[PDB]
Image (cartoon, rainbow, N blue to C red; front, side, top):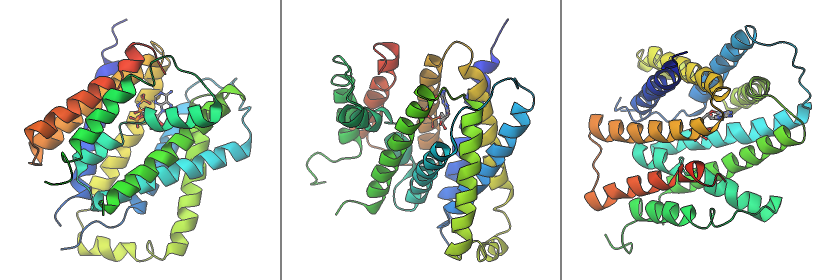
Length: 295
Ligand SMILES: Nc1ncnc2c1ncn2[C@@H]1O[C@H](COP(=O)(O)OP(=O)(O)NP(=O)(O)O)[C@@H](O)[C@H]1O
């Protein structure tokens, strides 16, 4: 049973996803792409329909034991995190976003330690040193010699909301014995409903066609971005059931490092050497916990 599709499928698709996301966000159209909610709405609905058409061809005996409200709260947290992350690209540069967003464990770790009252032996005190050193050497100058950018605040709030969603997921999985496809399916429906409800009130989507009228070449790319996102979500779901979940961490780390490399190469984003070694340090620490002492 050769399974090369476990690597290629989740690698090439997410690589195209990242390249498209960078293309349509920082594209020098002049009217910058200030709209951050429409694309996440489209992505959510596309991935939801793909989830339905996928579960239709999978096991049916499973019965969703999860209650309604937990999915709703997890959906608000998840959609808020995604919206805040995407809206921040107007200030910061792409490589900084994909690096900062990648340090997911630290928010979850601190939230669990302060709230869940957990314990981790010399693992959340050792790899954290490498992670924080890398982050605080890459984006930061030596001594602020050569108010912080508002995008950093948005990224920090995104990390906080993402940690909240993660802890919520952990609870609904442990104490309620939820599944994998059902969870993502329900949270997607709730998130898209809430996003649409808010959007119609915001008075922007009614005004969003005119922007499309200005540049008719912003429809195919966004559709492809949604399609690849949904395909990648389905592929990662299919992987996680095989070889356990530990492979997912290494897969994502490799994908994000190659995404950094492609971003710096293709789009000519300047980077300094002393800065450049910053990303490798944080990436090495990231996933090292998964390889040794998962936590
Ligand atoms: N059991 C799972 N394992 C991995 N990813 C999952 C799982 N369940 C849901 N996902 C989603 O799969 C995506 C993984 O991509 P990513 O945004 O990089 O998260 P990640 O934690 O950094 N990578 P990963 O360790 O595989 O979850 C996210 O959108 C997760 O919400």
